[PDB]
Length: 221
Image (cartoon, rainbow, N blue to C red; front, side):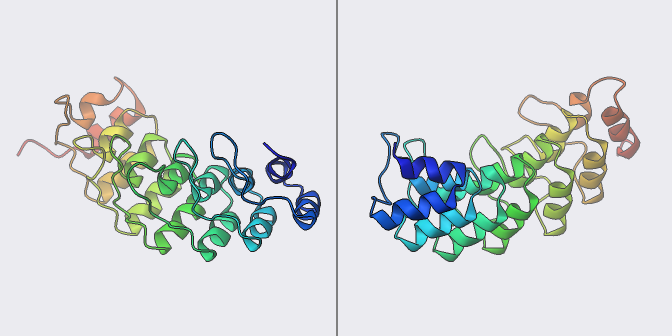
């Protein structure tokens, strides 16, 4: 790990540009194949990221753990970083063995980063194995604004993590607004998951979430 890595991690633009000017290797990576660009993006430091990109940093570089600069930018929640990476040719949706930027953005409630990725043609219903769709992640982590936006953009309401629907995920949490939003957008309140459980079955007894499900569930057909 180099001085450039550290300047990038800290968001120390003047030090970073000074080091670049001296001729240090912009693309030097650690044993985990982490570049200075990876560290700038993880810190959400857009000016440092752009300076590195201007000097030939690899916009689609992959760490040993499958992280790209774009994934790291989605960890930080810096929309500015996401934009500059995409400007320099970052791939928005990645192959299966690489960490998914949009799913991390949604998990952390970074709605603007999510919208930018969707605007750059990431599949709104992209189901990462065992993680689920963006809507499923949003429901798992009680990201109300992300849930609302995804539904409005046409996310498949029942598409989650194989048989676990977004409503099943929401039922395990404590957010009532998410329950009504899913229901309003046509969620199937009756269907059962891989454990044979309905959303109502999953809700905590006497909880507000359970109450919401009870109030929205139609009568026996």
